[PDB]
Image (cartoon, rainbow over all chains, first blue to last red):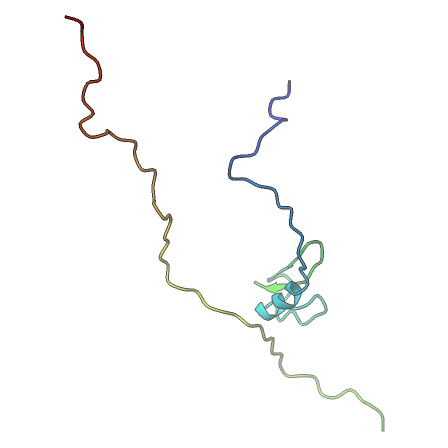
Length: 63
Length: 51
């Protein structure tokens, strides 16, 4: 009765449990080439990727 | 003496900081592949018949 519903992790698999700052990441993504949600994407909003980081949309790295 | 709208910009520059790609070496494993199980040298029989 529990088939396919009760699974088990492989030996190498693991759950993430650490918590980090993730505050300097939005400022690094912009150095890398992302353009903030505020504007000037430099393309057409259709040739651009919507960047998300943990629910918060940094916004529109060029394609 | 106030601020007025000026001419529209003629272009936009977007700056980002980016590093480059190295050569493809693809060094898959320290001791690589699945090394095969194998024969211990000589071994010898560890059993004899009676008589």
